[PDB]
Length: 113
Length: 113
Ligand SMILES: Cc1cc2nc3c(=O)[nH]c(=O)nc-3n(C[C@H](O)[C@H](O)[C@H](O)COP(=O)(O)OP(=O)(O)OC[C@H]3O[C@@H](n4cnc5c(N)ncnc54)[C@H](O)[C@@H]3O)c2cc1C
Ligand SMILES: Cc1cc2nc3c(=O)[nH]c(=O)nc-3n(C[C@H](O)[C@H](O)[C@H](O)COP(=O)(O)OP(=O)(O)OC[C@H]3O[C@@H](n4cnc5c(N)ncnc54)[C@H](O)[C@@H]3O)c2cc1C
Image (tube, rainbow over all chains, first blue to last red):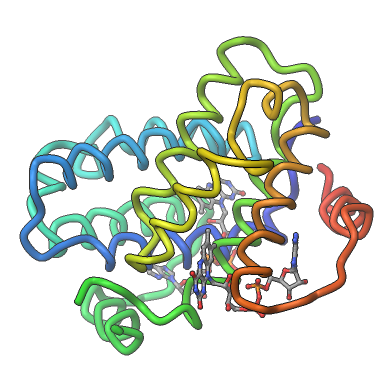
């Protein structure tokens, strides 16, 4: 019983991590790509819910949600990828917020510093 | 121009990561220690704020907030360590919340699955 109910960390986890993708450079270096890739892989090892970890790991290594080098090309590809991952999880949970990738871009860019 | 104002990611970041520490095993294996250690080091590479990343990296490599092997001993040590890191950032920002470690444990344990 090492897991915590999603009520406390679920949304915070999504918001923080979407913000992370929007802080990615428009034109990243080889180091930026390596660092962010390692972060998102490690993220799967620490989600406070076993089933969540298993599902996440499956998503980032299969289909269009797979974390590949193409996903790390730029801010656009990284933000789109995580957006897709979030939708993949939503669908598995039988929900769909009908939010377009553009709605998300407009939302997070409103917080650009 | 890659940063985001803290209003969107600050609180979410603390909440999600404190939750991560409470999901850590009571009696971790060498593998668990390595995986969580790598995650918390990588977290410093992706905060969407330049000086925030620098401060965090300095906090986890020096002083009482250093991420040493002892911090990874068990759930108690890892959760206390991140509570200390949060207080270190608070002190740097001249913010005082007065929350005790016991208050934090009570809050997150109430969501124990
Ligand atoms: C990596 C990760 C894996 C998870 N895996 C599981 C799991 O396997 N099983 C389980 O029970 N729970 C899982 N969760 C939790 C879950 O996805 C929810 O956070 C939770 O069920 C709470 O639901 P919610 O309806 O508040 O919405 P969230 O999905 O918490 O609410 C997110 C908010 O973001 C918006 N949003 C919706 N879709 C998108 C999108 N595609 N992009 C950007 N914003 C969007 C809306 O504004 C919405 O209110 C996971 C969380 C994370 C962070
Ligand atoms: C690693 C990291 C580094 C950051 N660096 C900076 C920075 O350099 N400059 C800047 O302006 N902002 C920074 N921020 C943001 C900042 O820490 C706040 O999140 C933000 O100012 C909003 O403040 P808030 O009052 O909601 O409090 P947070 O500090 O967001 O609010 C956390 C909430 O957690 C609780 N809490 C407070 N202390 C503790 C504790 N020790 N342990 C557990 N819970 C506690 C209270 O319930 C509180 O409402 C950083 C965030 C992270 C996640």
